[PDB]
RNA sequence: UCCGGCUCUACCUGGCUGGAGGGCAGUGAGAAAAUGUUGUGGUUAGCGGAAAUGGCUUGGGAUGGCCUGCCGUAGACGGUGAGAGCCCGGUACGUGAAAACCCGACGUCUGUCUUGAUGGUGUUCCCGAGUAGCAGCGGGCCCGUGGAAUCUGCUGUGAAUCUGCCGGGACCACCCGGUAAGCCUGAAUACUUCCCAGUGACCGAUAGCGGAUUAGUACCGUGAGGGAAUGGUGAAAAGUACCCCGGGAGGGGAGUGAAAGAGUACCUGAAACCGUGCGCUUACAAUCCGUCAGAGCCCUCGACGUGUCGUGGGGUGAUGGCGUGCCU
RNA sequence: GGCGUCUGGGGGGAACGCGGGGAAGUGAAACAUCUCAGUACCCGUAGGAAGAGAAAACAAAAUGUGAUUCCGUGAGUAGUGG
């Protein structure tokens, strides 16, 4: 899906346009991902509830995978025909990311 | 008699064609051209529209209640038009829209159209759009920029010369054609028309005999 | 073509019964089974796949406008917080199958003609029998019993084999064509329960399949059988934490949110219908309920002057005249 | 006929096919012959397609055609018909 948990991303669209972020979880069945520090919502939880500021899911087509060189870059797929993997790869450099 | 200069992508001219007089000095008959394009569009149009009348719907084949004594009106099926769920009456049906325009009216249309463009100097010729056997749309686009500035344009390239087709296909305005299926709507919708020389020769020695 | 033996038999011939090189053909309708190679041949999962975090402004959000670049064998389509060729999914294009399945391809395997043919010459024999034909009732052929052939069904009767027989619209003679009553035969043709991919001058929740919602369900009927209704919050639930009235429902503040004239009875939110306020009018009057004249009061625009007529306009409208709903 | 063994068939299906049976309301301004229709429906059996199919055929003196089927025309004609 060109994003996995543990990757790092750059936000495009929203009030939080221009934000780095770490991916925490993804929801591939609906193309949405919960990035850290973005989409802050003041959820009410009643117990002893409280107005608490939590994350919410971006849609995955509002984030570019940050290049290993620290710039927003696309990603693509070579093959290491020996090992038979399909490595996710930037389309500026060609490196392993 | 109108003359055309072939044109090259590399920035030169090869030769000149001396177009016929009778194909390309016909006077247009606007009613004729109207009729024929209307026919083309009609035959394009497919008749996928059908509805279920009173005799194809579900049920209704029982007189729902008495004729008399009830108080209410008289009814013979629960699927008649005036009900809610009932049959369409005079509905659409799957039908054909083609109409049989003759060969002479058609060809008269096409010749008159090509004349309308020729007199106004919108028929350009060309040997090719490309260098050898490798499509590149940037080439054809630059060449049409050299040769033309209008929005829309027609291209007539034969079957074997697939590279020009594959090249110019993706452009916004262009609408490519083979001269064996040369028609009238596709001509008139345009502003300029780019023939290949093979195409002209085929067209002319196919019609003229 | 060579021979093995056979023509009852040893011997000359003619004719069989065997094997052999060979040829032909093959899963054919013309006999039939499996065999193993086998084609980037096809189907049954998929995969890569070009190019802008571009600049100013608006806005909650830019995918908009304007200005700058690029790709293009890819500007088809869709989605993404508002119309996205350059975000995403994917397209043009090229790739891909251990196994199974289908096409042929082969080599097996199987037969099969090979011991043979071209022509000569005068006469006997055979050429599909309860049938063809004829008569009686009937069907269907353009043809309704008509002069009515051909094709036929049931009964009854019932012939010949080539100078034979059946037809050429009654029938007869001549000529013509053809050789019944034994059998198989592909391709063109018709069709879609299901499956795959798309198109639409087709519908868009009283439409379209009866069924966008648990739908042949609920409900009805003993039973066969009939047979409905209900789509939309917003960009994401951030679905109102907390306080006050109340038993609770429900609500008011405080909040979220771009907007709560978006609150899980939620896009917009008409009319009928139900009411609350403000102005005029209405309790001595006979009203298809209106129209023409119009007093009086209230609102308004404008020229002026301490309030005031006007090439005015609008709501009500005392009172007078006229006036017998709409359709078929 | 009884006993044992071996192989088949048995039912479902949306249409399409072939053989058989087989109506009526309707039209005729009534109606029975006729028509509606050999339709609907029912039966028996199939196949991926079926059935038909190699002349006991056409034709008209033309020195002609050469299995069958399905499409276009001939033709709404020659004709048939209370």
Image (cartoon, coloured by chain):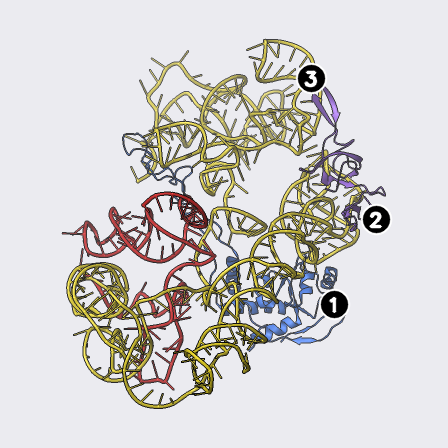
Chain colours: A purple, B blue, C yellow, D red
Left or right, B20 with reference to C242? left
Q: Where is residue C26 in the image (x, y as percent from the top left)?
A: 52, 66
Q: Position of residue C245 (x, y in %)?
A: 62, 9
- Label 3 lies in what chain? A
- Looking at the image, which residue is at 74% across and 62% down? B139
Do we see residue B121 in this rendering?
no
| Residue at the disc numbered 3 | A47
Which is more toward the observer, C35 or C78? C35
Q: Are marks 1 and 2 in contact (CB under 8 Å)?
A: no
| Residue at the disc numbered 2 | A93
- SS type, badge 2: loop
Q: Residues within 10 Å of mark 2 (few under 14, many from 20)?
A: few
Which is more toward the observer, C206 or D82? D82
Q: Do the residues labelled 2 and 3 touch (CB within 8 Å)?
A: no
- Label 2 lies in what chain? A
Q: Position of residue C321 (x, y in %)?
A: 34, 28
Discs 3 and 1 lie in a common subunit: no
Q: Distance between the residues labelled 1 and 2?
A: 32 Å
Q: Nearer the viewer, mark 1 or mark 2?
A: 2
| Residue at the disc numbered 1 | B132
């Amino acid at each position: 899906m060109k994003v996995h948990k543990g990757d790092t991303v750059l936000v495009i669209s929203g009030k939080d346009k221009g934000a780095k972020g770490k991916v925490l979880v993804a929801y591939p069945d609906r193309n949405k991902v919960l990035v850290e520090g973005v989409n802050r919502i003041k959820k009410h939880t009643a117990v002893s509830g409280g107005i608490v500021t939590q994350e919410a899911p971006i849609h995955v087509s509002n984030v570019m995978v940050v290049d290993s060189d620290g710039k927003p870059t696309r990603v693509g797929y070579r093959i290491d025909d020996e090992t038979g993997k399909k490595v996710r790869i930037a389309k500026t450099n060609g490196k392993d990311i | 008699t109108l003359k055309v200069d072939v044109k090259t992508p590399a920035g030169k001219t090869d030769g000149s064609v001396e177009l016929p007089a009778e194909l390309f000095d016909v006077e247009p008959n606007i009613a004729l051209m109207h009729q024929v394009v209307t026919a083309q569009l009609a035959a394009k149009r497919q008749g996928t529209h059908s509805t279920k009348t009173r005799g194809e719907v579900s049920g209704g084949g029982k007189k729902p209640y008495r004729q008399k004594g009830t108080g209410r009106a008289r009814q013979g099926s629960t699927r008649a038009p005036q009900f809610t769920g009932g049959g369409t009456v005079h509905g659409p049906k799957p039908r054909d829209y083609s109409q049989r325009t003759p060969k002479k009216m058609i060809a008269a249309a096409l010749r008159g159209a090509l004349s309308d463009r020729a007199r106004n100097d919108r028929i350009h010729a060309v040997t090719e759009l490309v260098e050898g056997q490798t499509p590149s749309t940037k080439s054809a686009k630059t060449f049409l920029g050299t040769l033309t500035e209008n929005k829309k344009v027609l291209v007539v390239i034969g079957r074997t010369d697939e590279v020009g087709a594959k090249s110019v296909r993706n452009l916004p305005g262009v609408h490519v054609i083979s001269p064996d299926q040369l028609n009238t709507y596709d001509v008139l919708n345009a502003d300029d028309v780019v023939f290949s020389v093979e195409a002209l020769n085929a067209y002319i020695s196919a019609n003229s005999k």
